[PDB]
Image (cartoon, rainbow over all chains, first blue to last red; front, side, top):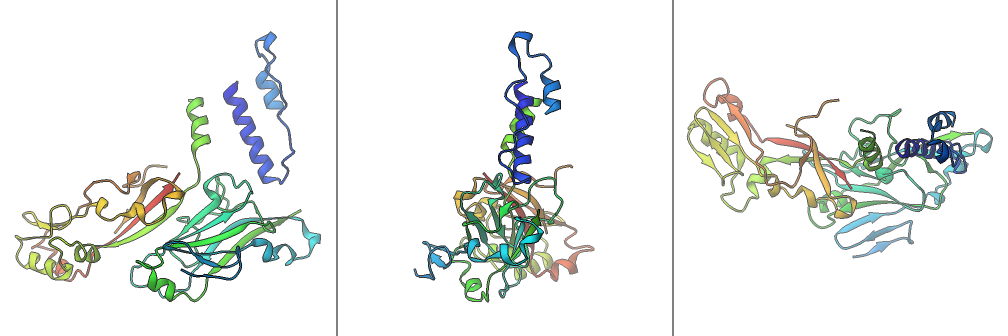
Length: 48
Length: 145
Length: 97
Length: 48
């Protein structure tokens, strides 16, 4: 999960670089809900 | 030893290294075309032409760097000029590359410094710099709305 | 594999591609230890297929029916052509003759 | 996709770069007698 959310924020960073918009925020803080073992993390990240 | 012009738009010798400088805000590239066709005017690619009397099988050594605060993802901030005749640093120039070209995404009207520096002013490249007519920059940019 | 791919994507940067033209006449002429001119030592070693030229590892040598011309890359000082502030890993991409 | 020849050679190593000609006295005597010089285009990459 740490690796793939790093890849997601990497793609978000190049989105902010190409479209000249440094405030574009598609990958929300969350998606690892610790009480349900971080399940549905990849569903939330595919949504983003 | 000497220098020429003002700071950030002139020549300067630093030790054994001549550099020629430029400010992109002082070129007014953002007002070459009318503003009705887009405001995000960002550099795609920059290539350098040095019309000098290159000897038989003689190399060029020059680094065109950027001095400023723009992001410029990684080592795309500088190129090395070896051909001297309409080159970037790259071997086989490739627009629509998967990776970012050097200086790609530079906002063409920023208050940055575009410095081209020559190694070896008095050593192996005295004759090249004495025969240098001018320095020519092909600034390729993109006007996007 | 994903840790290694992440480290690759975080550590891969662009380049500084430099071509450097090396002529062996300039290297053999400015070698300061058994230095020689190339065009006459090649005809000396080809019209008599025995001799050598220069020092070892930076000179000519005929071995049987095979002339070889040698070079040491540490003796070219390619790593100090550009200033060291632009990177230290300076590795050959390609060599053409 | 594959590595070019001599790719990744550290340009300041203490290695030997030898160019060797087959047939000094046979089919390639005239070529070596007419040889002006040997020119090497060493293409390298400066990376931080």
